[PDB]
Amino acid sequence: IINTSILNLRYESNHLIDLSRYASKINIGSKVNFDPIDKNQIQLFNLESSKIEVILKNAIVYNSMYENFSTSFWIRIPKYFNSISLNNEYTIINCMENNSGWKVSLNYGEIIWTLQDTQEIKQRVVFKYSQMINISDYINRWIFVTITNNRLNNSKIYINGRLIDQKPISNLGNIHASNNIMFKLDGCRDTHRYIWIKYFNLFDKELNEKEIKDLYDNQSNSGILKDFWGDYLQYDKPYYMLNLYDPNKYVDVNNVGIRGYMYLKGPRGSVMTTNIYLNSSLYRGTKFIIKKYASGNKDNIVRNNDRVYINVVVKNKEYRLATNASQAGVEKILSALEIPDVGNLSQVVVMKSKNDQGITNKCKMNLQDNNGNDIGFIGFHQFNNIAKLVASNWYNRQIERSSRTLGCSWEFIPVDDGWGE
Ligand code: NA
């Protein structure tokens, strides 16, 4: 599908370019930022010179009553912090000329798609997300957007590959879109507002549900683990930990050493600005730092099946996550060990991805002994009314026997400007 797209905006050979057969010209403003870790991730600020303009080849300029078309892209929208963002819809992707064409716009907790013909007939499809929520799947996290348009039926908006809303557009007549596509914050009153965007595509047909799911999987880069926000998980980067079975708890340490243990304690508390957002605090607990087991690779991205060590930060000092698997029972309680005294304790962790129909960017950690034998996925277990962190082959066996397992799925949360906590 990507090879058949009429616009394939990608960053390669050290420049942003249209990879389609049309090779439409790209005009990049001076205040456009490209992520050094992944230059396909584009940051657009609320500045006149923070814009990208695509000069479409004349053959693909939309001017039709009947041609179906679709668009897909990923977006990461920082949390709205101020009341100035209320009741302020602002365009981000503009293909309107004389108020005919299409455009993508944003508002407080909304992603909006608008179609309008040449006779003042308009239709909108909207995806709504709340900021009054403990843990949000959408606030400041990478979202895959797909919008399809059937001129004889409906316009549909998809989020992470799932249909969210559809509205009829068959009453619209001739849609004559703009000769260009302007990626730019237009009409936003929040001077600090920005967006992240990547993998923009334009299609000259109505994508079906299977094609959208396949695009969502192909562009997810499943061989690379992700942090909570959807960026690449990295080594040597401090992360606040979130266990998905107990989202209201955070990781803490009950004394350093084999005599102590790591556990989950709550509540997290809340961060809030009245009438704007009310969420669970994410910057809580002892931070984890992922360390390389194979130092022969210079790259700092954590990939699937990588073996790692887990460092634990306690009072600005780093310790080693480990356990003695010879302890009684199937739930091996984890401790934070002094790095010089790890000895032969089990500490090697195999990082894994976990992709189901729930929250994205799940990670799993399979602890192994120094001989390579599985100790079990890292989760937690109730000991004396305390949720102590454990490694248990019980988790691994349920997955092997097609049983559902919860408690061993984690998210790594780094400090990000889009969260502001
Ligand atoms: Na270390």
Image (cartoon, rainbow, N blue to C red):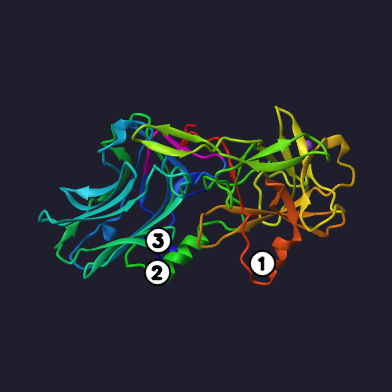
Residue at point 33%, 40% (across, down): 184
Which residue corresponds to the image point at 73% horizontal and 51% vertical from the top-left?
A: 390
**Gap between marks 2 and 1 measured at Cα:** 28 Å
Q: Is residue 9 visible?
A: no
Relative side of 240 to 190, left or right: right
Label 1 or label 3, whichever comes before in sequence order: 3
Give the labeled residue for mark 3. Answer: 21
Helix, strand or loop under label 1: helix
> Looking at the image, is mark 2 or mark 1 earlier in the sequence?
2
Q: Report the residue marked by disc 1.
A: 399
Label 2 sits on residue: 209
Q: Amino acid at mark 3?
A: Arg
Which residue shows up at 86% across the image and 41% down it? 342
Residue 351 image offset from top left, x and y in percent:
69, 53
- Tell me the kind of residue under disc 2: Glu
- Disc 1 crowd rating (10 Å Cα; few below 14, some 14-19, many 20+) is few
Residue density around tag 2, few if under 14, some if 14–19, many if 20 or more, within 10 Å = some
Outermost residue to the right: 343
Mark in front: 2 vs 3: 2
Label 1 amino acid? Ile
Sequence-first tag of 2 and 3: 3
Residue 291: give x, y in percent of width and height. Answer: 73, 42
Residue segment shown in magenta: 27-36
Whether 258 is drawn above or below 67: the answer is: above
